[PDB]
Length: 49
Length: 48
View 1 (cartoon, helix red, strand yellow):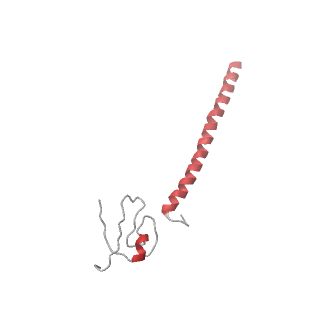
View 2: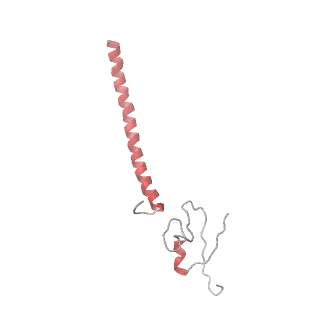
View 3: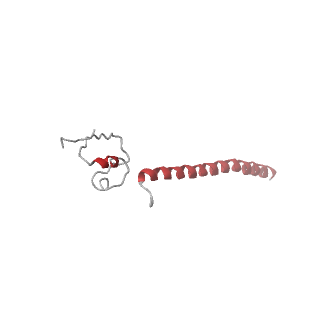
């Protein structure tokens, strides 16, 4: 904003938002896949207990 | 439908646009970026 008008700043900020929103989707998808693995391990540990 | 109308100089027609900066778009007629209208501008010589 400091060095650009709104008409063009909306486009530049929208690009950054899309990029960082993709970062969050990658993060959350991997946590779900990895949480299933620790859950399977907790099920094995409970069964052995 | 809002019809706005005025006269401007010859090398000023490019300033009538969403998101611009100039001596006529600063504080005389600021067109917002939610602009769904249409700017018509034609040469007016001899009448004006």
